[PDB]
Length: 121
Ligand SMILES: [Mg+2]
Image (cartoon, rainbow, N blue to C red; front, side, top):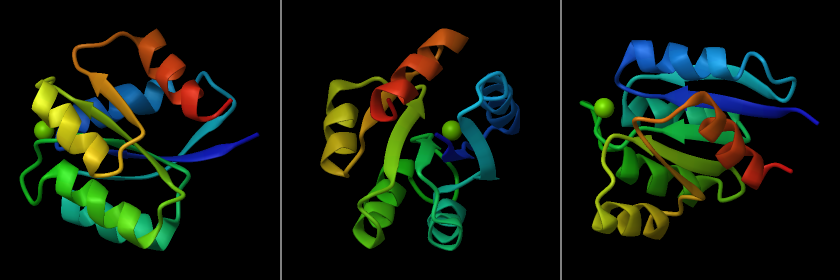
């Protein structure tokens, strides 16, 4: 019924935008956030969330490499990329890192829900 979401993005305004988008839904409860891949890896282990919204270019560590590490420890958590980069290769790298979804910025509110709802019917 409820899916514990965790938002990670180097842009703090971006984190707020998605956090507000998930507020109208009953289902997506935001449980934490991070601005870099390394903090995301530590928060993912501690928190043990059902869903991650991940940004690819971040200052501390790449978001794709963070995705691989997170899935290595816990495969069950579903990780969705949400990024300004839409290169075909990049998507290839993301799915090879264990990603379950790809969101291309710029987007609208409805797309975030319909993509998230694909993995959580
Ligand atoms: Mg970024």
